[PDB]
Image (tube, coloured by chain):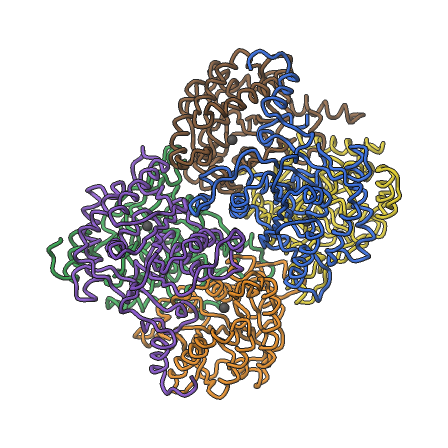
Chain colours: A blue, B brown, C yellow, D purple, E orange, F green
Amino acid sequence: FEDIDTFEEAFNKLLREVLEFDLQNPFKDAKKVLCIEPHPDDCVIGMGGTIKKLSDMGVEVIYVCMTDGYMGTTDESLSGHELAAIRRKEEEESARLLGVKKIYWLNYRDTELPYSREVRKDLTKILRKEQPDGVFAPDPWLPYESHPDHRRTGFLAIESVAFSQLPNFSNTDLDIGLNPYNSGSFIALYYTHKPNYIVDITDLMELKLKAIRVHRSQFPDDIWEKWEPFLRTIAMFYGEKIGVRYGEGFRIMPGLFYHITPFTDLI
Amino acid sequence: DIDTFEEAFNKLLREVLEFDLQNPFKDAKKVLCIEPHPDDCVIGMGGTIKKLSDMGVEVIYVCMTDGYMGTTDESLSGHELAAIRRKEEEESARLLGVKKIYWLNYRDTELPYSREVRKDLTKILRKEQPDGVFAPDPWLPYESHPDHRRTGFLAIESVAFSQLPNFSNTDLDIGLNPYNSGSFIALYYTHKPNYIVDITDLMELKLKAIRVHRSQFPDDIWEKWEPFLRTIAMFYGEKIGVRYGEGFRIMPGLFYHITPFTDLI
Amino acid sequence: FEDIDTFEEAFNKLLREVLEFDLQNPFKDAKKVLCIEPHPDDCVIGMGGTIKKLSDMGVEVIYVCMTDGYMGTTDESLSGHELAAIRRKEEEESARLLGVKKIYWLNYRDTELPYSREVRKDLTKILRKEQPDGVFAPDPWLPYESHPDHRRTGFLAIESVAFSQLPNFSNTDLDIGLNPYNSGSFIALYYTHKPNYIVDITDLMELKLKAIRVHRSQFPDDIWEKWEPFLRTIAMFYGEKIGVRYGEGFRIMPGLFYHITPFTDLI
Amino acid sequence: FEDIDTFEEAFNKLLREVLEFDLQNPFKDAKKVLCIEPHPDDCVIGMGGTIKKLSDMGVEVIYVCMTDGYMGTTDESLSGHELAAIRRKEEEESARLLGVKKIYWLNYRDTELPYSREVRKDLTKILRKEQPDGVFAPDPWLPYESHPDHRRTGFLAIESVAFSQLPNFSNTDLDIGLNPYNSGSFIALYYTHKPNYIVDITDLMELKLKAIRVHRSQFPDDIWEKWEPFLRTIAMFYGEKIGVRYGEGFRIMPGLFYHITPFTDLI
Amino acid sequence: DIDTFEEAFNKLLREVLEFDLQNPFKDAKKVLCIEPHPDDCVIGMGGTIKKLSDMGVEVIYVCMTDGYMGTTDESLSGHELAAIRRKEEEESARLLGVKKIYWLNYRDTELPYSREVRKDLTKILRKEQPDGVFAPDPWLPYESHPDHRRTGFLAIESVAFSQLPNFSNTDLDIGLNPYNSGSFIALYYTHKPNYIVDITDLMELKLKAIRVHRSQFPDDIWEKWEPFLRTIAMFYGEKIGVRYGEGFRIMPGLFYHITPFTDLI
Amino acid sequence: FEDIDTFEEAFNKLLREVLEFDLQNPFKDAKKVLCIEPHPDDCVIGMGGTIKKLSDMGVEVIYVCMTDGYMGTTDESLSGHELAAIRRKEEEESARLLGVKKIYWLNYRDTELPYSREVRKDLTKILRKEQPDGVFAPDPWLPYESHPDHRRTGFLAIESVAFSQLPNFSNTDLDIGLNPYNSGSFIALYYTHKPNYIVDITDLMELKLKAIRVHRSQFPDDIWEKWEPFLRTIAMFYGEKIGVRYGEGFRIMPGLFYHITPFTDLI
Ligand SMILES: [Zn+2]
Ligand SMILES: [Zn+2]
Ligand SMILES: [Zn+2]
Ligand SMILES: [Zn+2]
Ligand SMILES: [Zn+2]
Ligand SMILES: [Zn+2]
């Protein structure tokens, strides 16, 4: 469009017409979604109430869990293998409370999630098989996020959603009968410092806290004394943004903005 | 000696550092423009490249990868596409006056982040000894192409380390010199440009040389990308009151290390 | 909680009451600290002043130096090996002046610091042996930090401080009779663009400068022309923030804020 | 079996009864096989006549080709990408002469085949999908084999055939609907210094040479002047072993012998 | 001085090297038996281990991996299996008199071949300072388990390098000493044993302690493996005229480096 | 061919006529050679004698030393860095005695030589610059060789000699105006258990020994007691094979026999 007079107009036409970007009800049509978590519990803690709301509407929610949570205990007589047996059950129970379908366990070791083509391939296979309408994953640009598994899951999820659409990427998948990942599915990023879409989870907050504490191994009383205020405060930082008590924040952008975009901060 | 930080900084920039952004490319005879994929040089600084050629600067591309993955055409393999994209780029660069292209040949979506790639770029720096280097800004927020983050990091690193005789010393052992210490670094694809080039006059050219990457810009995909790319050129151009612009971030060499007030330029 | 009215109230309760956080005097009880540095001289440059005052208060200050500084010369006649043996001597004398106990050399090669589990296990074994009260390290989120040794030292430091506390992490340390790293120690990040604790070093500035120049292989006369003003200017950026002439800046935060936290900018 | 009197008897009962190992007609029942090659052309050069014989009998032969042959030319105006386009066509044409079904291209770069869990996963997916009755691959113990791609394909093929049977190995495959690789398929190793099964390829030798030269890019006249004597001599080393002019040799052992077996040299 | 190679070699072995295979474990108070998976120590040298315990030697296992992949039971995950296999191994080792087990915890089928693993074993060598080390022979032909090749290589390497103060120096920095220089290395699972232990008397014990790894030896799988394992014990036993034996390859430390006549022992 | 009667006849025709192979005088035309060594001293130990005779004939002999020898000391007071600077001095003087031109130091760390494309590119750039007539390197198939630096130097050497001849391999070398490595050069492997060419060094033995001992950091009196007999014994193992007192052994083969060849034991 050669004759438009200001950046601001252009950007506006770009968002609303060219890209028809819409934060009003961005999960309106979804039938199936994947929620990707670095560790068992992260989906519920980041977006449990949202997962529930989706379930409630008849959306199929599938988990993909990058690691086994092997490392997450201070108990010197609980091995990582035992912990991981336990966290699997804990996540199955938590997810059942949220109406969640199915979990894909990638089984990478807790704290050792690689950042590699290999991991992109695992996700790409799930993506291609399930062809979901939207994907959720932690925002790897969250500042002071000191857990490598979190930053890497984030990155790998965004990369995989783009690359799994390309037939020459992980090409054996197509050779065993899968199609590339279908275009026009959304990415939504939770655990974000810059959300631009909030789900009100005021009514659901006690459901979320319950489903979080089901991961008992992660949440004994002395830990919960700190974690419950923390989780509640986080939910209020998000909710206030839409004038409600408790929210879950997401960052959702048009696919182009994840690449060469110097004005991403205008959504 | 000096009283305030505000004063101390100013003196740093202008006296001690000589940092000056009015004409940062006025003394440039040879430059490298480093791109992660074929087409990134033209999309991100195609108009500036034209401007540099027309001025007589020699402009040399270094493309990190082969564009192998860039198609949804299931009847086009990566190898075929890679061979087409080197053609596309050769024609695209002629239009902008581009001399020479070094292809490193890493696979698209697979550019490593490692000492090996630093050694490939170092060997080129030491060979060509350019006056300035262009590369994507590795800090662009929400940049989710690893090839992009990786390129910018490795470019800035390599410009530094290629200067060190003990770094990839085999280069010296075979007759190369360490990379000269006077050169500039300019990052394109940047959210914090502190230097903008007006390409309002060149915009139609820029767009034609982009379109020359036909594998990347079929008809339906240009339906979003021409509007996208104009909208970005307006973003940079507005910063200096022109229609279309190209944004570059530039900084004294020092600021890339241990510097808490980099947002002051 | 659960009754608190607003996000602003929750946040302040969380910070001060639940998490017991305050930056009045965060090094108060410290008997032993590790100063983790990517290259010989980084401890002196970013926190040389603070080290001295810690020595002065009778705190045992220990260095961990991630790499050998192999690459840090433009002299064609000086091999990397020769340089490393020099820089070690330089560090030892620079550290004498700051009253510095003892230095662990990891001996990774300058410019080639891995970002790997192996390096966490190196840090972890040290933390488990020393059991420091506090650990200092570069902020790996510093804008525009382009030395991979710095960003990587920073992230590895934060990660090791968490993981060294887990008994299933690097479990052989335990099998050889080291204990998990003790829980309550602090983290302080230097070379930072968002400091929230400032140490006045104004009275110490000349000693700091002398202790840096002791790295003569790094600061001959021609480089010192650029670097002395630079170093003075950084120290004034930090000093200004609390109204003293010369300062050293540090970023400190509750432990929980290193993970999924979306309002880390409020401190 | 507690009361057997010599090693030699035991070993004999072990082979013939316990393991019912049979080198008489070891491909008798196969319906589908995979032939794994490091580069395009290796299946034909190592075992072209055998592939043909299998085709002839109605066996489905599927290729898996580890690399793209990107590196295999001395022509300074033929890029690796062009070479690889060309070698794909060359292999399609060669394979058509041998009755070959289908080729899986892993697309790893020629000379850069990794030795990694990732590559095991690609093979494991093909194995699980196709469930073939037997697999062929170069013998990685062939002495003085100086091509890394050859040694690694060999190893990876033997490992994958064992690991793809295990449900916890590459577990996402089972989560997208695949079953583990079925038990009791044979491995046969070509390019071997110790074959214990030879296929007579006297009648087929000229077919093989033709299908080898179809890879024109690899076989110009000046190269063929050396390669044709070489290939013929190799085929006679194998054939003489069964008193025929030209053979293809394989090493075939019972699955147990690929693990902890100190008497493998007795077959 | 000396006239023939045959003479020069002999003198090497016996005078200069003191290499002597009649009772190589006569002076051994503590030994490490390094296994790639839980059960390899008992399968490969279970009877010898028994013999060493009964003699008073302290026997310490170092297991490289967790056995995570070792089941076709689709209702048993790797983590569950790993937790069962550590139990299995604890019971199995008690029966043979085994003290202590170091678990390194790498995943089964994933043991890296790297400096990191050498540092884990080195830390144990330096801690425990054993008199001898047992490990699989990395040269077994047709050994196709990477965990197996990898273990033997890393064991022999680590025994060497743990002796070097500059190697994993942090160990020293925290109070450990380099690994003492007097110790032996013996490779089991070997096709070229030059020392055989008669375990004819212990064979039923060996087999019971193997069976204790019940996850690995259901009924139908033991239908092949008991015959397999007896057939291997006959292989080694025949070498010295006994019914069942365990084969070890042993060599002067020198022979592991630059030695063209290693087949002469 | 195609008419030849027996395998034994084919093989001898192949070796002698097609491949022009013979070990009468394989270094005849050599003007320039690389002696590739894994650690400082390996060239002198395995082929010190042969080097001298090459110098003596006026051949330019160049060393490539893969690593710095950092680890090679039991002295707790001598750092790896210090050792490397020493060993370089030792090499330089040891090489003066063998009339050795010039040494390329790659500077990988003793014990940590990668097995990677990066290292082939290091060798390749050297071969393309020097264009040697011959390359000497350790046999990576030596029985029981337990130093990973040796096996890896050996395989990397053979691989680089092939790949450096391909223009698409490390193509940037070409873009900077180096040529592919010239085709007809020979490969000779030392530290070998199957030598097929023997150099009489009997008259040179005392000089060899002096040139090794010049590595005093490696051979103090106590280690020399073990090592002098050892070195004498190896030289007699090789000498015996051609009826001289002291020899150096080398394995040489046609190029084709480095790949898929099943009768490499016939030479
Ligand atoms: Zn998590
Ligand atoms: Zn790009
Ligand atoms: Zn530094
Ligand atoms: Zn091949
Ligand atoms: Zn095992
Ligand atoms: Zn050596």
Task: Tell whether E212 sits left or right of A9.
Answer: left
Residue C117 in view in this figure: yes
Q: Position of residue C247 (x, y in %)?
A: 79, 36
Quadrant of residue F40 within the rendered picture? bottom left
In the rendered view of the protein, which quadrant contains the C terminus of chain F? bottom left
Q: How many marks?
A: 0
> Viewer-proximal residue, C49 or A156?
A156
Q: Position of residue D209 (x, y in %)?
A: 20, 49
Q: Residue drawn 81% across and 25% down?
A: B3
Residue extending farthest front: A58
Q: Is residue E201 above or below residue A246?
A: below
Task: Tell whether B142 sits left or right of B10.
Answer: left
Residue C76 in view in this figure: no
Q: Is residue E84 above or below residue A129?
A: below
> Viewer-proximal residue, B162 or A234?
A234
Q: Residue drawn 77% across and 38% down?
A: C248
Task: Tell whether C90 sits left or right of B29.
Answer: right
Q: Position of residue C73 (x, y in %)?
A: 57, 39
Q: Position of residue C261 (x, y in %)?
A: 74, 42
Q: Is residue B189 above or below residue D113?
A: above
Task: Tell whether B51 sits left or right of B18.
Answer: left
Quadrant of residue A191 within the rendered picture? top right
Quadrant of residue B1 within the rendered picture? top right
